[PDB]
Image (tube, helix red, strand yellow):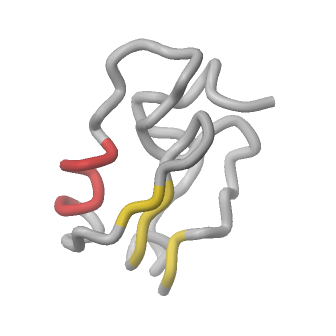
Amino acid sequence: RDGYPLASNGCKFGCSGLGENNPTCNHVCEKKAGSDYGYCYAWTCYCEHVAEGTVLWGDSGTGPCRS
């Protein structure tokens, strides 16, 4: 299951312009998603094979990500 639902209106995984060092998006994807498919454009991070039952409400970069 793809991971582009952006459940958390604030942020899904790492990657966040207006935020601290939240590069977890890398390990996160290759950890629970066990895949190297990530998409970061704005203040947030996307991934594949993460929405397959897993959770999605902000990782480390979450918080001051997007409104």
User: In this image, 37 relative to 48: left or right?
Assistant: left
- In the picture, the quarter occupied by the C terminus is top right
Residue placed most toward the observer, 40 or 14: 40
Which residue, as the protein is rendered here, is positioned at the far bottom? 1
The number of discs equals 0
Asked which quadrant contains residue 6, the reply is bottom right
Q: State whether residue 22 is above or below residue 24.
A: above
Foreground of the two, 3 or 32? 3
Task: Report the front residue among 65 and 55.
Answer: 65
Residue at the image point whose x is 54% and y is 30% from the top: 62
Give the vertical position of 30 relative to 27 (above or below): below
Left or right of residue 24, residue 1 in this image:
right
Q: Residue at x 33, y 71 (%)?
A: 37
Residue beneath the point at 19% across and 49% down: 27
Q: Is residue 30 left or right of residue 4?
A: left
Against 53, is 10 above or below? above
Q: Judge left or right: residue 49 versus residue 7.
A: left
57 up-or-down from 5: above or below: above
Relative image position of residue 36 (x, y in whole percent): 23, 68
Q: Residue furthest right?
A: 67
Q: Position of residue 39 (x, y in %)?
A: 46, 59
Residue at 23 percent across and 73 percent down: it is 35
Q: Position of residue 34 (x, y in %)?
A: 19, 71
